[PDB]
Amino acid sequence: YVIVGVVENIGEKEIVGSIFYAPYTEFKVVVDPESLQPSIG
Amino acid sequence: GISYAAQGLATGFSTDTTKSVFAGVLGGKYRVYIDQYAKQDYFTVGYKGPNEMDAGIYYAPYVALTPLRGSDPKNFQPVMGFKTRYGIGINPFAILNSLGKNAYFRRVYVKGI
Image (cartoon, helix red, strand yellow):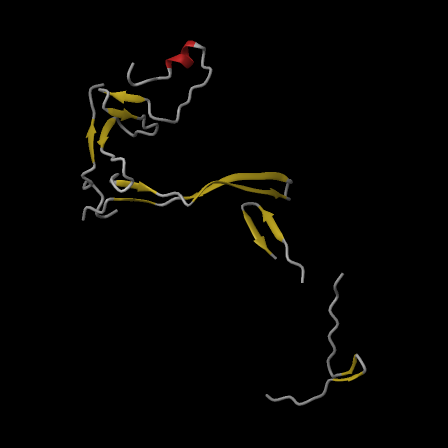
């Protein structure tokens, strides 16, 4: 398909959009040394 | 006693046992080591020059005694260990070209002991 639409702002705020995204931080990467397999999540 | 059993340790009542290295030199010529995993009974004679390229067999460690660590939440028991990466090989003489072929070594099966 094809989509046409608009994201727009008033000053610094991206107030206009069909979809909005708001990440919550305080991308966390950790090592999990479970058993013999210290993988990264 | 040219080939040793570390008799000094025996004398001192096992002050060590050091059971990991070549025992000593037979004939004043051959450095001799115990195969602690020998399957039947045997000896192998081999040559080694001072040059690392004159061994006939190679072991070329990349990683050695690197610790491993962690924990098991099922019971929260520790995980500890060791890894190595070394590789082996021989003077090609052409593994398939190794079996019974490497001139640097001669293996004799021993019976009657």
